[PDB]
Image (cartoon, rainbow, N blue to C red; front, side):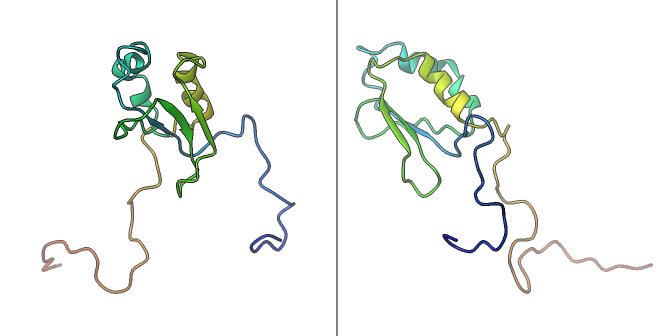
Length: 126
């Protein structure tokens, strides 16, 4: 009814914890003095395992957790300069989805017509 849906119950409806698709941790890494624990986990490698988590090193702002959709909206922006930390790391691993190096990236022939993938010259001689 909003865009184009004939008959599909009504809405997607949350399955469990309404996991998110994207989320970025825009930090400056300059708070190493104040929040030496924050980046600490970042240096650990735990967030690196989270595909749904970016972990950007913004120009020079304050550490803030961001949960986006895809375009860049930003569903939840919370300052982690003291708020809770630590558990925050879990915030992502939990609210995010461990696709496991998946991500909808290039795979097979995409929408194309004609030539879009060369490969030597098969002479073929049965």
